[PDB]
Image (tube, rainbow, N blue to C red; front, side, top):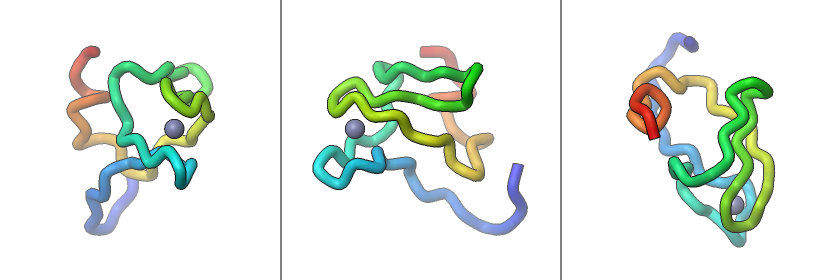
Length: 59
Ligand SMILES: [Zn+2]
C-alpha cells in the first residue's frame, strides 16, 4: 500500500468520460490496468486500492 491519509474515488482519466470505476469495466489485474467500458480507455490503478469494495469484493 501507500502510507499517508487519502481516499479519493478513482475517476476515468478521460475528462469527457469521468466515469467512476465500475465492475463492468475490463480489469486486467494481470497488467494492473482496467480499461473503460464506455470510452474504452486504459487507466492505471490508484496508489491506495486496499480499502476499495469494488476490488476487495468480487464483481
Ligand atoms: Zn472512460
